Image (tube, rainbow, N blue to C red; front, side, top):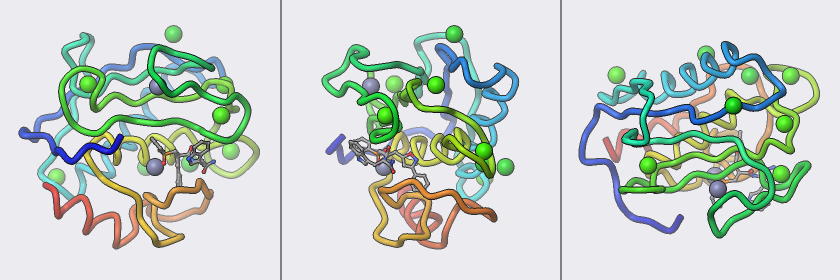
Length: 159
Ligand SMILES: NC(=O)[C@H](Cc1c[nH]c2ccccc12)NC(=O)[C@H](Cc1cc(-c2ccccc2)no1)CP(=O)(O)c1ccccc1
Ligand SMILES: [Ca+2]
Ligand SMILES: [Ca+2]
Ligand SMILES: [Ca+2]
Ligand SMILES: [Ca+2]
Ligand SMILES: [Ca+2]
Ligand SMILES: [Cl-]
Ligand SMILES: [Cl-]
Ligand SMILES: [Cl-]
Ligand SMILES: [Zn+2]
Ligand SMILES: [Zn+2]
C-alpha cells in the first residue's frame, strides 16, 4: 500500500464482485455509489459501475485470508483495506465481512463511510493527521459532510 502512483485517467470504473450478508444488495450498491459521489463531487473524476474484472476498482467482501498477504482479523480491528492506483489488484477495495456492516447511527460500522475512506486510498490518497477528516486512520462515526477540508485538498492535489 506504499505506492506513489495516481490514475492516469479520470473515467474510473468499479465492479462489485460480491456482497456482505448484513445488508440488502440495493442498499450496498447505493452505499458505494454515494461514497464515490463524494469524491467525484470535488474533482473531475467520474465513477461508472461495470461488470468485469477489467474494472479499475474491484470491490469484494472477505473474511480472514482472502488471497492477498493481508488477511482480516475478524470482529473489529482492521475493517477493510485498499490498494493504491495501478494495474491488477492495485486500486481494489476489500471489506472484512466479519464486521457488522450497517449505516448511520447505531451499532456496527457504516459501510458508506468506510467505503468512502477505502475509495480514497484506491485513488492514491494517504492518511490525514486531522482527527475529524475522513482519511484519518481510525474510524469514527459522525453526521454531516464526510469530506473534511483536508480531504478535499488532498484529492484535488492529485486530480
Ligand atoms: N477500526 C479502525 O479504525 C481501523 C484501525 C486500523 C488501522 N490499521 C489497522 C491495521 C490492523 C488492524 C486495525 C487497523 N482502521 C481501518 O480499518 C482502516 C480503514 C477505515 C478507516 C475508516 C475511517 C477512518 C476515519 C473516519 C471514518 C472511517 N473506514 O475504514 C484501515 P486503512 O486505513 O484503510 C489501511 C489500508 C491498507 C493498509 C493499512 C491501513
Ligand atoms: Ca466532478
Ligand atoms: Ca484494480
Ligand atoms: Ca476486522
Ligand atoms: Ca458482516
Ligand atoms: Ca448504524
Ligand atoms: Cl455475493
Ligand atoms: Cl450521501
Ligand atoms: Cl452512514
Ligand atoms: Zn485484501
Ligand atoms: Zn486508511
